[PDB]
Amino acid sequence: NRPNRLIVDEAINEDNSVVSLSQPKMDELQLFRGDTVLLKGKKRREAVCIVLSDDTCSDEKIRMNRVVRNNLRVRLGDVISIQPCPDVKYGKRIHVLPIDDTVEGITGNLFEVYLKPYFLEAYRPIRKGDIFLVRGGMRAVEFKVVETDPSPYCIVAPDTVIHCEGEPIKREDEEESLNEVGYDDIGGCRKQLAQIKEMVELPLRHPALFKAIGVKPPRGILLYGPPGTGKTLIARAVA
Amino acid sequence: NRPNRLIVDEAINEDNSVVSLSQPKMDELQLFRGDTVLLKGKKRREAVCIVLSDDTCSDEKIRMNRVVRNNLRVRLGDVISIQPCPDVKYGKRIHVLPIDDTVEGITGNLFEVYLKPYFLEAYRPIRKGDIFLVRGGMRAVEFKVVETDPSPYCIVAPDTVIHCEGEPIKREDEEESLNEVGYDDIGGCRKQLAQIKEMVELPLRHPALFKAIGVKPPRGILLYGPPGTGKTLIARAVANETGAFFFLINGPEIMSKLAGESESNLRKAFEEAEKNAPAIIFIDELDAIAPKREKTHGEVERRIVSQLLTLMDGLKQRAHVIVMAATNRPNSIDPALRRFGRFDREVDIGIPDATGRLEILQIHTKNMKLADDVDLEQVANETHGHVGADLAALCSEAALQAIRKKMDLIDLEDETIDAEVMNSLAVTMDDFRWALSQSNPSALRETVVDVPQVTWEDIGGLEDVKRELQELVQYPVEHPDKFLKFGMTPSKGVLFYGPPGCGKTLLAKAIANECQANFISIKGPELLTMWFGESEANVREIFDKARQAAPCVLFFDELDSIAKARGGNIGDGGGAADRVINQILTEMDGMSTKKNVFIIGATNRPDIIDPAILRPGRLDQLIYIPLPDEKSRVAILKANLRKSPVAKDVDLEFLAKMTNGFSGADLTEICQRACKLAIRESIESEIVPEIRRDHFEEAMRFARRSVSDNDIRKYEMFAQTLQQSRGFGSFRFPS
Ligand SMILES: Nc1ncnc2c1ncn2[C@@H]1O[C@H](COP(=O)(O)OP(=O)(O)O)[C@@H](O)[C@H]1O
Ligand SMILES: Nc1ncnc2c1ncn2[C@@H]1O[C@H](COP(=O)(O)OP(=O)(O)O)[C@@H](O)[C@H]1O
Ligand SMILES: Nc1ncnc2c1ncn2[C@@H]1O[C@H](COP(=O)(O)OP(=O)(O)O)[C@@H](O)[C@H]1O
């Protein structure tokens, strides 16, 4: 059954480039703990991150964060093929710049405030064309890789230096804005959010499944609770 | 009279090619049991099937299924000529293909999934041009015969092989779609569906009969019941199975229009169906159409109500249309529509029982398969407060959860699903039990009507009372001649008084199962709710519900509950009269004594009962239930220990002896406590599967009698005062 494809799931860690996998799952690939793992999903984009350890997730699934889901253009309930890449790679020339939608109203240097306390003692394989978000400065800032040395063989290292011009770019509709709501913005609602997740996944992720079969999917989903609980937040996140 | 033509009827078997006939009917044709029978109806189509045996259908009729009715283009209430055909015929070349309306979204092979497990060891004479439906793959699939070897002399056999091209065809309006509703989609509704069947057959199947005669057929047929019972399902089935045009009028659809247009829609909805006579006009809901009870608001609402009223009584024959309506709340209809000529027939359909609910599960799961450990008998017991629509959602959720459990890690990234996996998808107990927890019943506050399954074998002792009850409610209903000849009226009701716990509720429940009648139970707090709420008019609906549900029995538990709430033995500044019992007394005077209804009153304090109910015409028969004796207590325990297998060393005859003031209910908690010990010790020793003697010995320490010792003499002194059979011992005459 080609045991190299796993189903995605929401991550429990607050870090950006972290992949959560179980101990029994990790030995099936015959791989080590501290390394770089390559992820191939759909839409001919690739993703490489750092794999971690888990012990309570499931029998066979992958837990990946929201920022790394945007690079692969994949969503919850989708299958992705994972393959290892045990090769040593460094970085020589890195050219990145943020988008004006998040750096509008910010002056001064853009290196010692967001680029230095982000990549220190991290060793993250930043791939070309990836979009990552940095948290700090009591606001949300996201960057993008425009051009660099030809990928692969690109990892941020202290030997290389970062340079930026200063002018932003214009984004398109191909990528999804990280400022929108998601599954990581819901707290406390664990038992009740799962019912909505399972009631909506089938009739949306597989529209053709219900079109052929005669099973009647639920139409109306009425929400309750005192004002301010987040009924609109859940409705927007599940969409 | 050419005894070869029989009337059609619905089949009771779930098989497709089965013809049901009685044993006396079968010898009239001089034919054998296992063979092929030829049926000739109308429209120059023929049909051949396999005849079976029956013993409870009728004197002379044929019972045939719905799929075989479509081939002959015949409906219920039609005559068909049957003739035998004793000739051996085989099959050589068969070419069949389904229609795209049912195989849209299915890929893979179409032979080993639906054609092989359909014709094996069957030997069905499939005729050319016939349409048959196959059930499987958790969906409905139907095929059709396009061309083959020239009929007759065509029977499917293992020697021949089946071939299919792959491209579908396009159907026409000549054949009726099997995906529509029918008479086989109704479960539990047996007594009430027959009234609609007989009320609609004559004015639709024979429109010319009523056109020549002056008999006035019923026009309006109002439907009742909580939402989800299937009022629309019945309305569509009776229109599809009678060949009449069905028109659906939604409640909010009229209201969604602006001023004037909503008025025009109702007017234009009548002559449109008039030209297509016969026709049936159905109204979805009437709460949002004519809520003229306390609204008294809006200028267009009254205009719409009056337009509907004028369109009701304005049907001066002309066509042969029958108008039907459905309302969930019987009390939410204006009396103007209830007048004669608009709505004179009322049908009240209630929540089905366990037997009725099991048929709903069988109906809604006929297209899907189930595992061997899957039984629908258990799920029909815990869903006591579920409506017929709740079971459809329950089975749909059970089917859906299977996909999320078995088709979660597969991730078949395909544009169209296959059939070799969908058929193999089975549903187990773990799928249904999860759906039971998530299901929320929508009908748990209304008064449910059910026939209890308790018989006289479950009541221990009290043999003297049973004969008195069997001789009071069963003779006037089954020997009316001896009551009409003497001219003396039967008794109205009976009163049960005595110490609590003797099982007065069981006596009322057992008499309902023997008489094959309904049973309505009212508890104590149900009466106090109206007394505290200052609304005594709610009992009128309770009385009216029992009337239409004939035959029925009425039960009133602890009628003295209101008297105890105002002082009890000491009473208060007033008398023994209140407002709840006043309405019951007023309604018992106006109720018809000729109906198959009965009222049973239960009480435990006869000293506080209002004497206004004992005077002749309301309640005269008083039955006293004394304390159980030693010989009667053995039977109580024997009947109680029937649900759970017990050992042989349990000497119940000994337990009967030391029990002196223990009532019938005083022994149930003893058995419950003894049974709890077995579970406790099994779970404790898990880290044996039979009840032991020592369990009953331990339960004797907590033997608490619910009745005291001072009130025992009060019942005896009351009974001896009421009877007083002293003085006149034995008198004789000199000659
Ligand atoms: N459970 C929650 N978790 C995170 N944020 C929340 C939650 N509930 C409410 N909020 C925040 O409160 C703001 C207002 O929410 P609101 O529209 O009032 O929710 P609702 O429509 O359910 O009352 C939103 O912008 C949302 O970010
Ligand atoms: N007694 C029943 N037997 C079979 N199916 C039923 C029954 N009652 C309801 N259903 C199913 O429930 C669905 C919804 O019915 P609904 O329109 O709510 O009935 P009503 O209009 O009487 O409330 C229908 O598609 C029908 O198939
Ligand atoms: N004579 C009897 N035979 C068998 N079981 C009895 C008898 N009397 C009472 N019970 C059991 O005791 C239980 C409680 O009855 P209860 O409601 O106290 O009766 P009542 O309302 O007449 O006092 C019932 O479930 C019934 O099974």
Image (cartoon, grey):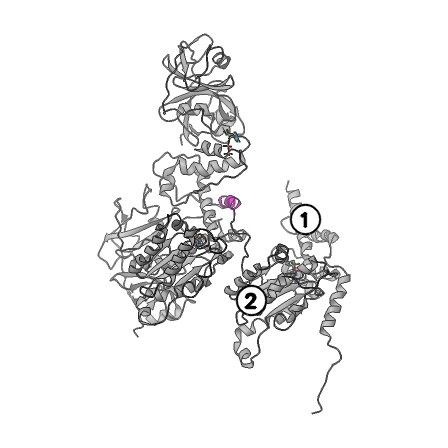
Query: Which residue in the protein does label 1 denote?
Result: B677
> Helix, strand or loop at disc 2?
helix
Label of residue B514 in the image: 2
For label 1, the SS is helix
Residue B72 at least partly seen? no
Q: Chain of mark 1?
A: B
Q: Can residue B216 be seen at all in this image of the molecule?
A: yes
**Image quarter (top left, top right, bottom left or bottom right) of the C terminus of chain B:** bottom right
Residue B213, image x and y in percent? 33, 72
- The amino acid type of the residue labelled 2 equals Glu
Name the spot of residue B647 as percent of width and height, x first: 65, 55
Q: Is residue B102 left or right of residue A157?
A: left
Magenta range is: B429-458
Give the residue at x 55% y 66%: B514
Q: Nearer the viewer, mark 1 or mark 2?
A: 2
Q: Is residue B314 left or right of residue B552?
A: left
Instruction: Please determine if labels 1 and 2 lie on a single subunit.
Output: yes
**Amino acid at the residue labelled 1:** Leu
Q: Is residue B29 above or below residue B287?
A: below
Q: Is residue A166 above or below residue B651?
A: above
Quarter of the image where the N terminus of chain B is located: bottom left
Question: Residue B444 magenta-drawn?
Answer: yes
Which residue is outermost to the bottom?
B735
Q: Residue drawn at (54%, 70%), measured in percent from left and top?
A: B592
